[PDB]
Image 1 (tube, rainbow over the protein chains, first blue to last red):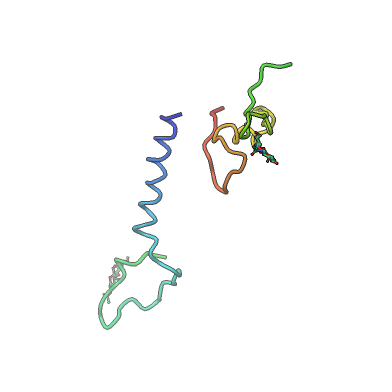
Image 2: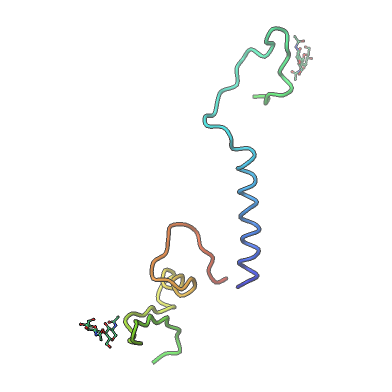
Amino acid sequence: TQLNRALSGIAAEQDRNTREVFAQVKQMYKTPTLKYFGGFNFSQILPDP
Amino acid sequence: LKPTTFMLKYDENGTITDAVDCSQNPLAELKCSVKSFEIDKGIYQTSNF
Ligand SMILES: *[C@@H]1O[C@H](CO)[C@@H](O[C@@H]2O[C@H](CO)[C@@H](O)[C@H](O)[C@H]2NC(C)=O)[C@H](O)[C@H]1NC(C)=O
Ligand SMILES: *[C@@H]1O[C@H](CO)[C@@H](O[C@@H]2O[C@H](CO)[C@@H](O)[C@H](O)[C@H]2NC(C)=O)[C@H](O)[C@H]1NC(C)=O
């Protein structure tokens, strides 16, 4: 019991760590079509649709 | 009479007031595990299959 409870606790805090870093976004926003914002080419940082 | 496992609640004077058959259904298998008659919403760990 102690073992199972120990590993599940260690495992469950790995999902807490991932949401604490990434999930700071309240709304999903769309990818704009314009990526040369004043010449600033942003095609590499954005996802390729 | 069968060799099963029960959990027994004792009052202030040692009267068995309530019992849970630990092999009845997966709900009652959980109450025997966590030592409670009332269990909060979520996922809890129980025995392996
Ligand atoms: C911004 O950078 C992208 C690369 O991320 C450039 O896109 C490439 O353009 C060349 C020229 O036709 C193509 O052969 C490549 O296939 C393109 N890359 C991709 C991933 O499609 C883009 O040209 C740059 N912007 C400007 C204004 O030069
Ligand atoms: C355990 O037994 C005692 C008796 O010694 C109970 O105390 C009595 O309880 C009744 C009603 O519950 C009261 O009317 C009496 O006045 C109590 N007597 C004394 C001396 O306090 C006690 O209630 C029992 N415990 C439980 C949980 O029922």
